[PDB]
Amino acid sequence: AQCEATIESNDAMQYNLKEMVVDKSCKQFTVHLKHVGKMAKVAMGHNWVLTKEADKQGVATDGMNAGLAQDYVKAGDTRVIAHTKVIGGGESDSVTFDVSKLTPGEAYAYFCSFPGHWAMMKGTLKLSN
Amino acid sequence: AQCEATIESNDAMQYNLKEMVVDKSCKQFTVHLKHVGKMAKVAMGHNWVLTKEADKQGVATDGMNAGLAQDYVKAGDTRVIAHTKVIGGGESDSVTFDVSKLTPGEAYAYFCSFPGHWAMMKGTLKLSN
Image (cartoon, rainbow over all chains, first blue to last red; front, side, top):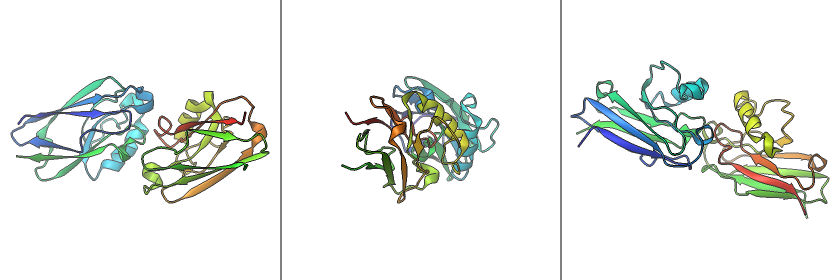
């Protein structure tokens, strides 16, 4: 295995992956997000945010409140392990994070914090071998 | 025949109608919105808002900032000809307005102003011809 994954987002407000597994041999993990549709980021922008499954809705709320210039993530939100920028159709963004931030056996939520998207764009991330 | 129409909204962020025609025989018109999904308004709330095609993005934006308790529509928004409340799955709302507010030959936009829904929940309303 290896320490990176590619996820796709489209114009129908969906990710193509519902779960991601980070190999235990990984010190760092890289998430490559692609926006496969053609809608503007102002209309159907997408990001990828990682948090404890618990913090999902709270980070989502504060994120909506941060605005597009903050990539719909409250700046310095400590419940956020990692996040990409918001991208529109045709673009891509990557984020690399320290695997040490994850706790083995625990589950994580990854979701899109662009306004209203968290309800449909959500998945699970877990650390496994 | 009637001066009424029922439009459905679901969990996939779709309206079941993409165009609505108001008969010239009507003095008034009623729109019955039904949310036939099973998601709560906090996650997939839907409303029906009618504006001139050009006011769509401004009304949506401003409605966004008004909040859920305001049905995601700014109070006294003069660009809004008519709107229902935001409803969740299993609920319905009706709105009646004056046909004289519409101009024969003009295209109106109807859309959902819940955060991020306008891009997907939008249709056209016009007078009969």
